Image (tube, rainbow over all chains, first blue to last red; front, side):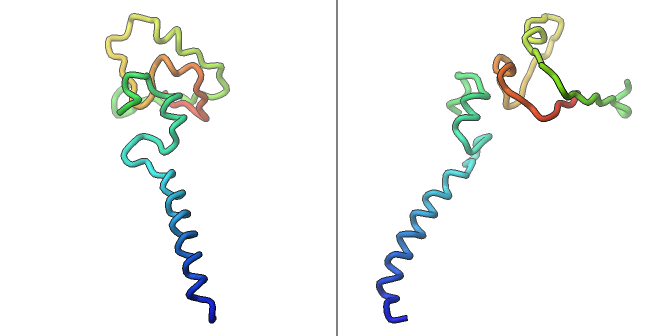
Length: 49
Length: 50
């Protein structure tokens, strides 16, 4: 338990990166969270929406 | 059939060709939600309801 001041530094970075990665599975209002389905499912005029 | 007794047909095990449906001119309303009609050919679905 002595090295906590050094361990939390690693923990914070590891949590921040994990949270950044988890944000790719969000729709943000779109119809799908993966960019390939939108391109393979919608016409070019309305994919940009 | 009637509105309150609407039929439902199960569609499965198909080489589904929607080009003939698209090229027909007998339909006054041709509207699709979330799928481009020209792109229906390549896509694969687990089941289709009619």
